[PDB]
């Protein structure tokens, strides 16, 4: 009980640390879902002056971790599929919404959508979770 | 075609801040083929002394970028799937190999596999590329 509670607190802590390092802020969060935001900076732009896939993945991963933690269900991604629809340019404010779609005994499935300030879809993620 | 692939790779590496920042090195190039290497550092570990997904994704995406641009035609990722198989511990040396599976005039499919120093598969990646305008930057 207190051990489980301690583990949830620890999971939250590590998640907040990654968010801070990435400049991510929680906008909304409840049971099974989290909405976080991040502003693309010149530092995270690739050769094409757009946010590199690695940053986008990190943003999505952070929103997924928050969605797991909202219910004390710490998990790691075992697989993930990503569709890039529009580039994330410098200055853009990206909002990532993660939502649980299925929660089994040991695994689960989470959906994550990233949109820009114009409310247009930047990328769609669907990941399988472990534990 | 290997020499052309290398020329393009050298041109892209010169302006690849993300790759250098991550300590990614290019060790092999050919038409639709790239091998990249990176050492897992403590600066990229999670709460389990294991490498972060974002860093592994970046390594696979780097091999993918170089392989799908080795032909001299600027291309970008429109989609991709990743499977994490084993953790990446500090000090581990990760090698990412990208092979072309298909390459049309516009679209392409490349398979990437990340292996550690013990020859164990860490992750499997598959991405679809889309060419843009002209020559690489």
Image (cartoon, coloured by chain):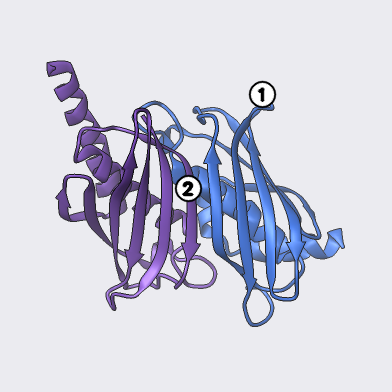
Chain colours: A purple, B blue
Please tell me which residue lies in front, A27 or B56.
Answer: A27
Query: Residue A10 location, x and y as percent?
Result: 21, 29
Q: Nearer the viewer, residue A8 or B119?
A: A8
As drawn, B1 above or below B106: above
Crowding near the residue tagged with mark 1, few <14, some 14–19, many ≥20 C-alpha atoms within 10 Å: few
Q: Chain of mark 1?
A: B
Q: Residue at x 52, y 31 (%)?
A: B88
Q: Residue furthest left?
A: A2
Q: Badge 2 sits on which subunit?
A: A
- Left or right of B44: which side holds A62? left
Q: Residues within 10 Å of mark 2 (few under 14, many from 20)?
A: many
Residue A121 seen by the camera: yes
Quarter of the figure with the C terminus of chain A: top left
Residue A9 is situated, as x and y percent measured from the top left of the image, at 17, 30
Above-or-below relation of B62 to A117: above
Which residue has dot 2 on it? A80
Residue name at image x 75 percent, y 76 percent: B105
**Can you name the residue that lies furthest to the bottom here?**
B133
Task: Tell me where residue B44 appears, x and y as whole percent.
Answer: 43, 38
Q: Quadrant of residue A43?
A: bottom left
Cα separation, mark 2 vs mark 1, equals 25 Å
Q: Residue under circle 1?
A: B118
In the displayed structure image, the side of residue A109 where residue A2 appears, left or right: left
Q: Residue at 22% x, 42% y: name it.
A: A16
Name which residue lies at 23% across and 38% down: A69
Q: Quadrant of the N terminus of chain A?
A: top left
């Amino acid at each position: 009980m207190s051990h489980k509670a301690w583990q949830n607190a620890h999971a939250m802590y590590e998640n907040d640390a990654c968010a801070k390092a990435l400049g991510i802020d929680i906008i909304s969060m409840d049971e099974g879902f989290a909405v976080v935001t991040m502003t693309v900076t010149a530092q995270m732009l690739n050769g094409h002056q757009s946010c590199h896939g690695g940053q986008l993945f990190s943003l999505a991963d952070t929103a997924f971790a928050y969605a797991c933690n909202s219910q004390g269900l710490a998990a790691v991604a075992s697989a993930c599929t990503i569709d890039f629809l529009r580039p994330g340019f410098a200055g853009d404010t990206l909002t990532a919404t993660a939502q649980v779609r299925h929660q089994g005994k040991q695994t689960g499935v989470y959906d994550i959508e990233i949109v820009n300030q114009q409310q247009k879809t930047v990328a769609l993620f669907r990941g399988k979770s472990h534990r």
